[PDB]
Amino acid sequence: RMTWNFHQYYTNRNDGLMGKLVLTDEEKNNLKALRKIIRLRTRDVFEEAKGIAKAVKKSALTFEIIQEKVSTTQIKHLSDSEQREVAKLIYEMDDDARDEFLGLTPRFWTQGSFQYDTLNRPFQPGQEMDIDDGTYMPMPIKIGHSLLILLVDASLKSLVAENHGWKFEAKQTCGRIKIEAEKTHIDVPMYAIPKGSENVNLALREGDRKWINSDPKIVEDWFNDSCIRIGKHLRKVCRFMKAWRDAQWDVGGPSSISLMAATVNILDSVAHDASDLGETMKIIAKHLPSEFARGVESPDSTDEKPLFPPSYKHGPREMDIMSKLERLPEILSSAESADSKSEALKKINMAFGNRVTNSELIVLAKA
Ligand SMILES: Nc1nc2c(ncn2[C@@H]2O[C@H](COP(=O)(O)OP(=O)(O)OP(=O)(O)O)C[C@H]2O)c(=O)[nH]1
Ligand SMILES: [Mg+2]
Ligand SMILES: [Mg+2]
Ligand code: NA
């Protein structure tokens, strides 16, 4: 009969969960500003390296002179051996390769939650907002993997040198600048593309494969198609599931993309009503454990691994994730049946953290 309704608690843009999660325009503009700085520097580093290559096209300069030239650019912020390597790579280029490099101008495209608007304000101390800004290198389906990575690293490392409180982190799939004071990091995955999703190649930092075909547009188009198909509330509930994950784990938990994929599957196959996103979240929560136990398939069919493994592959971390997923619909049910508004709030905040504090967003209802 009587039940607490949480639709405002979730959706209210003043001080409900959407209000707590969505970045303000100032914050978004700050991120855009950070993105521009990184893009400009990467553009500049490539122009600088191209200037050296241009000089070598004109005259077959000695190795020591090429090295000296490298030392005057932003590449000076790489290690000595890495500078030697860039100089050696420029020295060793054949005419064809050098011409291709002289024709290369990096392009950029943001992928991930800043692009499709699911980027949440961070919650726990230590957690950071993420901007995924890819750099793209148009090439014949002729510039080498090593040189390209060194130049993008030169870019990021040169900014890290100039800015107090910025730090560089090498990842398998990107370079990363972390800005702890701003609770932000920017990831720069690097792609080779033709000068056709099959030809978008993501550079890998280590291993048996230098490249793998992984077009971020596949996920972006899948998600935006899903939003059109299911409704705008898809973005809201994905934000909320990510907020749940940030509240349950300081570090770790299921990936954002696994939560998106499982949520889309559920909302495509189970009736729900966007006029009550509290019920919609309860419905999602009821079905997530089965989605995750069987393994969460990627929306990109070319991915070699699922986004979350099936339960026969579970270790302590996946077991912990299954446990918290199993608890979530119980938390939501108990909040619905709580004795008072204040207890309803206390209970639902055990799912999403103590972010929403306004118990007037919770209203007595019937269901
Ligand atoms: N095909 C594929 N793409 C991935 C995978 N992981 C990340 N990506 C691509 O990178 C994009 C950004 O990934 P994330 O930073 O992990 O997710 P997000 O949507 O930005 O969420 P968050 O706000 O937590 O950063 C999404 C997708 O295009 C994956 O496992 N497979
Ligand atoms: Mg991201
Ligand atoms: Mg990232
Ligand atoms: Na939980």
Image (cartoon, grey):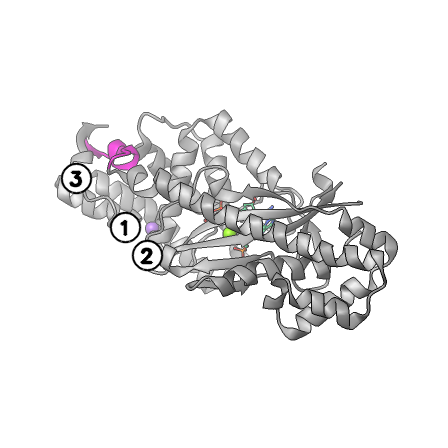
Disc 2 to disc 1: CB gap under 8 Å? yes
Residue 128 at what x, y percent from top left? Answer: 40, 55
Which residue does the image show at 41% across and 59% down from the upper left?
320
- Tell me: is circle 2 under 8 Å from ligand 1: no
- Tell me: is circle 3 under 8 Å from ligand 4: no
Looking at the image, tell me whether mark 3 or mark 1 is earlier in sequence order.
1
Mark 3 vs mark 2, foreground winner is 2
Which residue does the image show at 72% across and 55% down from the upper left?
51
Q: Nearer the viewer, residue 320 or 264?
A: 264
The amino acid type found where label 3 is placed reads: Ser
Looking at the image, tell me whether mark 3 or mark 2 is earlier in sequence order.
2
Which of the numbered marks, if any, corresponds to residue 124?
2
Task: Tell me the SS state at disc 2.
Answer: loop
Q: CA distance from mark 2 to mark 1?
A: 9 Å
Q: Which residues are magenta?
A: 1-14
The amino acid type found where label 1 is placed reads: Gly
Can you identify the residue that label 1 sits on? 353
Tell me, yes or no, whether the highlighted magenta stretch contains residue 8.
yes
Q: Quadrant of residue 309 in the image? A: bottom right
Q: Quadrant of residue 340 in the image? A: top left
Q: Is residue 20 above or below residue 172?
A: above
